[PDB]
Image (cartoon, rainbow, N blue to C red):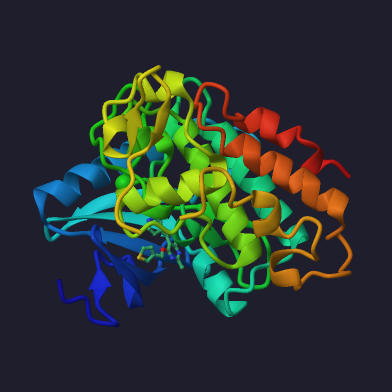
Length: 331
Ligand SMILES: Cc1nc(OCc2ccsc2)c2c(-c3ccnc(N)c3)c[nH]c2n1
Ligand SMILES: [Cl-]
């Protein structure tokens, strides 16, 4: 769809410029003459598939809107929606650039442990809000690109894009999440719950501090191999229940599991998170050596929280309320 700059919609919105494009369609900056403010309009393609996920996005955002609590404000605000020229249009507040752009701006050397902590605390609070029983929303696509600064000067963030989201027990797709941030339970073809967002969050926080993705698989096999390098072979009780366990692993005479090997990865559980983070070696690539708020003690707390977020078992993986009580967040 051609949207010219200066185009006026419905005597209300003046289109200014393109913010960006997705598989869903496009996001434009526009002036709202009624509220007298700038907004972001997400313009959904005139195709059944994209209309259908945007309709789910509108339903889930309107559901959140009716829960007035202290914890709903880490989610982008949907102001309203309308149908225009057979495109579903979602009107949001304007936010700023995304956390991937923040990383690119550091030349992928990563932000400080102190700024990582502020992001972690806001995202844990968002996930606690989505876990509200009457919401039980799984985001399903958390990644740096889907987390926006509220203001280019400041460290407030909001989660965007509920285009892949579902409520608990309303699963549609088996293949979900962006590969780098995809949970073991999704890789293993298992029924998934809100814990897949916490897995993504653990991956995101390590990446925000080191500048690089924790697990950058080129495909699902490579993804599971990179996770295993750091965390070891997933537990037997999980692999025993996993429809796609034999995509990656093999059950052994005595019902233990091992990697299926391909042509020539560090051996299982030997690419240690403590070395990735540089806990005892001045942080990622030693670049934090002697900066304040980057002591071994601060690093150990961060590492402890991440390993609770990257529990293989979605039953025992840390949950948002308990993540917020972790020592990493204690003054
Ligand atoms: C500046 C800005 N950008 C945004 O999205 C950037 C983007 C994303 C994909 S393509 C370009 C947004 C959004 C936004 C974008 C996409 N989905 C939702 N639910 C909200 C709201 N407010 C914004 N302000
Ligand atoms: Cl997805």
